[PDB]
Amino acid sequence: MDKFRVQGPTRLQGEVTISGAKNAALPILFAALLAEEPVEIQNVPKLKDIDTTMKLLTQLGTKVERXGSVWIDASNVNNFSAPYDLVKTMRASIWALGPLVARFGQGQVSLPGGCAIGARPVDLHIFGLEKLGAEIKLEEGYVKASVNGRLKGAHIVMDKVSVGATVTIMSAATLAEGTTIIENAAREPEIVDTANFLVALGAKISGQGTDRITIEGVERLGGGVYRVLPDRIETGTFLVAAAISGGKIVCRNAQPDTLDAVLAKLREAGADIETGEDWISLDMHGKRPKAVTVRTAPHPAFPTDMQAQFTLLNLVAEGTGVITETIFENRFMHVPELIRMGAHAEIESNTVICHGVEKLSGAQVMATDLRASASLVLAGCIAEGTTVVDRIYHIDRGYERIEDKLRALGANIERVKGE
Ligand SMILES: CC(=O)N[C@H]1[C@@H](OP(=O)(O)OP(=O)(O)OC[C@H]2O[C@@H](n3ccc(=O)[nH]c3=O)[C@H](O)[C@@H]2O)O[C@H](CO)[C@@H](O)[C@@H]1O
Ligand SMILES: *[C@H](C)[C@H](O)P(=O)(O)O
Image: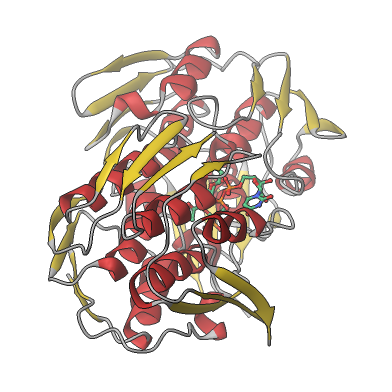
């Protein structure tokens, strides 16, 4: 298993060009299963989840090719059962189900994998497809969906906010007979991006970005070209990298309006932030951040995908800060690893009480998920000495070229094979 060896401390400063969103590219690639004509999806990041997705689509009979763009021809899709080996390596695999049943009348997918930060059920996806008329049965380790003829539009009220289920329902609804109204829909920027990609193929969707999405089903979707929006979590990660290291960083190919809460929280921490149409700069002026209070919640509130990174920020900040995680139940394992690097924190139910220290110390650390792993690498950049972060393949799932980007910002980093 590869590891990153980091020698700190190093100020992280300069510029970085943000890649397309991991979490918009994924639902768009699965939505392309609905397309009868060639599709070109632009600005797709080179991530392990994207590679897994391309392999999964190919196994269903999709013809896929990629470079910066990914080309999809789903005209000959003819196998409606997704293989367990690909399905279980990430979360996005659940999105194959709705498109398959909506377009072909049937689809089978195993329970997904992905960030091991909670039980992460898919009951809401099941709920929504059933509301659209699909029969759902759990057999042989598969979630099997089927319908005789078209799905039927429905007024669907979500009992809980779910990014994934909102995408599943909105996507399947595009080929349903009639109108679907999703109430209490997730508002994430990736949902807006997926909706607009669907519309480019001929779908009729309005309300994306709000809590109510209305879809008017059509007979079929064609093809088209669509550019994936910038990755707000990769952006937030590098803004935090500047903030915790006293540097100034300018993020290019950014979309400022997807980060209102994160930018506001960084300003509370003392950051001097400026934004333009497609860029964001952050200058800490060499100053230590001020501790802040953070509570994760559905977009547009502070994102759980920036939680581990802000935990690191508070742990090197001046004063006592708070991190409250309301979305996932097992997303604090980066904490004991940072404590081994010298941090001071107490976990109390779904909250971490942070007591910032001036400097962290290098150590052999490991996280079992994407954002926590990236956070340990940032901690290594600012700690004194050598930090070795094990199992960094987790980072490959969500960051394109994090090694080259961090090195361009000043990091002393090396990828090693290790034992
Ligand atoms: C591939 C992708 O886009 N991943 C993102 C997506 O995941 P994901 O789509 O899984 O996020 P969800 O919004 O669906 O989950 C939010 C909450 O709802 C629960 N839930 C979800 C679905 C369901 O059927 N039942 C249920 O109980 C969850 O386990 C969690 O406690 O949004 C998360 C929250 O912003 C991000 O942190 C993930 O990086
Ligand atoms: C970590 C939560 C990743 O984004 P997912 O793909 O598993 O959701």
